[PDB]
Amino acid sequence: LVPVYIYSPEYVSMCDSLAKIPKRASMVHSLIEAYALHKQMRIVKPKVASMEEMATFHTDAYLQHLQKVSQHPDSIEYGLGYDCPATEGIFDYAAAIGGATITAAQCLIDGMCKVAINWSGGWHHAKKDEASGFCYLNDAVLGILRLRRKFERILYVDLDLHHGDGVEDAFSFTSKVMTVSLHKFSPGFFPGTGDVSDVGLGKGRYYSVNVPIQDGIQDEKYYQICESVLKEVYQAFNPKAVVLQLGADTIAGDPMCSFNMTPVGIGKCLKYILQWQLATLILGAGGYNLANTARCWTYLTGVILGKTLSSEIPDHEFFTAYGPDYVLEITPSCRPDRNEPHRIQQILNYIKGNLKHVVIE
Ligand SMILES: CN(C)c1ccc(C(=O)NCCCCCCC(=O)NO)cc1
Ligand SMILES: [K+]
Ligand SMILES: [K+]
Ligand SMILES: [Zn+2]
């Protein structure tokens, strides 16, 4: 039907308080509203996740400590400290984002929509009892566990710059959820996991697909790799629902300065997934050039709505942040692509061999 847009003014205000991305949620929604895209979507207010719902993946012990420090020596033991500081109210922030993704997943299984959007979600590094990489709660896993009540095989596609290790670890032992992550992979780069030989464990073996990619990849080659993998994944795995993480830290201009992507390339990967006509949960999380992240997700929202957007950024609250040209398009950086053609073919062929075992159920 009409895409569902998870939004409430209190929810965006909560997401703006994250120290790593101040006011990014307001910038994203303000630009989407500036293009009047919210009038073409069904606005759904997100609920706050309960302790029972967060406990479907996270352990009690980790959730108790998170709730205590939210209002300590054992904080480092649960991954709280450096990348994830235990600030006041951090448990309610986690429950808010986790509940937003659960809400979007609930809309999918109720037949209310075929696409549900929660751009502020997709924190894919958190483990069942350990925070990691700015992630205290793994709302992506919680969203998958909610769709799992109705859909038998769920495909998780992680297009963030970083490896989605938390989601992959959560389902590394099952064949009922397949994780596919395209990410920068280089010794020293966070989180350091997700080589192409990472395929899963036990009965989940060959149901974890990882595409290690080097710096400087652009739209054309990226869609070549993504369409090649998604085509083989769709025919070998035959999914019934898709969870799509679209972190914008791959876009040119991001301080990560690794990939050299534009939203047009990500949108072509998104169009290929929407053509499957499946229930699709859209997440974001990643993105540290605030204006470029709003640019990307606004463009991707238009791709979902099938609309073509005006190049000029309309005047709004955060208009001054869209220099230097104040247009929606993003120009790739003039730096080399470090992806050798023979290395990419070697990675794709290795994945093709792994997926042949999936065609032998
Ligand atoms: C300049 N400065 C203080 C820092 C710069 C980079 C990092 C970092 O990458 N840390 C490793 C954790 C990265 C997790 C990124 C989360 C993400 O986007 N996942 O997709 C840390 C501090
Ligand atoms: K990824
Ligand atoms: K798996
Ligand atoms: Zn990232």
Image (cartoon, rainbow, N blue to C red):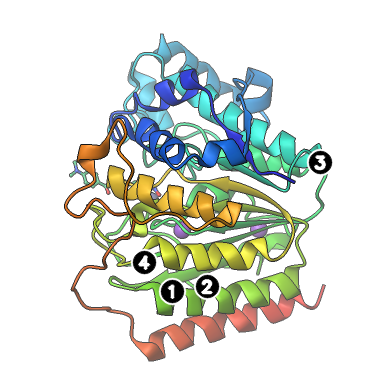
Mark 1 vs mark 2, CA separation in Å: 6 Å
Question: In the figure, residue 143 lies in which quadrant?
Answer: top right
- Tags 1 and 3 touching, CB below 8 Å: no
- Where does residue 244 sit, x and y in percent of width and height? 58, 53
Assess disc 4: are there few (<14), some (14-19) or many (≥20) residues with their C-alpha within 10 Å of its C-alpha: many
User: Mark 4 or mark 3, which has the lower sequence index?
Assistant: 3
Q: Earlier in the sequence, mark 3 or mark 2?
A: 3
Mark 4 or 3: in front is: 3
Whole-angstrom CA distance, mark 2 to mark 4, is: 16 Å
Amino acid at the residue labelled 3: Gly
Say which amino acid is labelled 1: Tyr
The residue under label 2 is which amino acid type? Cys
Disc 3: CA contacts within 10 A as few (<14), some (14-19) or many (>=20): few
Residue 185 marker: 4
Residue 36 seen anywhere in this rendered image of the structure: yes
Quick check: marks 1 and 2 in contact, CB under 8 Å? yes
Expressed as whole percent of the image width and height from the top left, the position of residue 4 reads 65, 38
- Identity of the residue drawn at 69% across and 61% down: 204
Pick the residue in front: 113 or 245: 113
Distance of mark 1 from mark 3, alpha carbons?
32 Å
Nearest the viewer among 305 and 54 is 305
**For this view, does 301 lie left or right of residue 143?**
left
Secondary structure under the numbered disc 2 in the rendered image: helix
The residue under label 3 is 111
Q: Nearer the viewer, mark 1 or mark 3?
A: 3
Image depth: mark 1 or mark 4 in front: 1
